[PDB]
Amino acid sequence: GYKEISLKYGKGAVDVKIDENMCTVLYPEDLPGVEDPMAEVSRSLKDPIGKAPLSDLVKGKKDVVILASDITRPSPSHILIPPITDELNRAGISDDSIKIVFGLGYHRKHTDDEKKTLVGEEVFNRIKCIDHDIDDCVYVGTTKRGTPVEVFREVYNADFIIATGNLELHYKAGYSGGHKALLPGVCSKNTIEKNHALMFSEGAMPGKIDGNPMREDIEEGGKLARVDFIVNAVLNSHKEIVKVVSGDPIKAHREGAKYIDKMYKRVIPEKADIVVASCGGYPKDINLYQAQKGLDNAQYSVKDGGTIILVAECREGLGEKLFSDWMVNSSRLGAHKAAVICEVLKRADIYLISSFDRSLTEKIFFKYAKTPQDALDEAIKKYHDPKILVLPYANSTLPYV
Ligand SMILES: [Cl-]
Ligand SMILES: [Cl-]
Image (tube, rainbow, N blue to C red; front, side, top):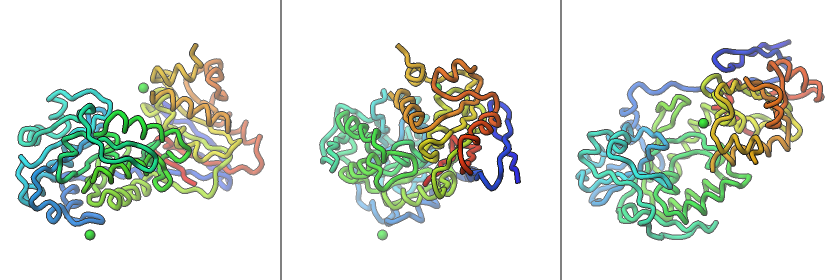
């Protein structure tokens, strides 16, 4: 039989026809956000994972620090933090025994309005909210891989440290959240630099924790810094909270990672021959830089010598300046993501179905085709009873071997 698959392209949809017994179509389970997010937080806190509830951990603490993400990495801190302070208050901790510290890493300080954006005005008024000061860190150890862990003094000073943030697939750390709120967020330039170098390894990839060297280094540095407790928001593709996990910085994170996996990880027997990947329509395919995200997910599942068919309009062009310059071999996140594309092209072919014309499409080293069918029908010929994987929401769907 012949299967007929709508693939979103730009602000509409194309179609492809594939022999069903030759292809698998992997879909995400993109769950909708909970109706009462702040109540899901409190539910989470009452049912913590791998560790006692806060009610039993904090009695007598006088210097509690809550880590939150900065304006750059939008997290629902304003949803997570108020229920946390409610438990801290309930357990006898005054608001003057509580501080919020923003994990800037390299980024600039926040204005006051940005701070109120992050935690809510009510929290900002009753609790001190401090930016990471990257020049005021204190050394607490060195990891097995040689990262010196140097932590902002205000976090160093604390007798209790709660880490909050998002928990999603991450292209290098495997997943965000857990100890990542601390390393690199509230660490010195030496710490960020040395940990950042681990992202260039073959084990730093989405959906991988054990044997991911960046994530293992993060969790090791966070242990040297004695993170006591996490509260993490598991986010859907619309960045809405679908679940909160609280408790042990490892066990609560692992349970959050399985909720993410149920939504977006899709385990395949083996790497397939042809991967047909849509970005899921505009604006996920608004430019090639953004479309690289579906392509990154898709290239863990293409065989050496395989063919990717990337269905992405790229209405507004190649995207971020560094990524584009690298891709056009002009005469640092963007540059890496472009080299990621180049490495895949050494292993496989990539067809680009886009608004680009043939000259430009082949300048940047993709195959050209006017439709997804034309690209498939062409490369289906170059393979022998091929396995064909179809990702209609490649930007959020991670095939995994
Ligand atoms: Cl326990
Ligand atoms: Cl961009």
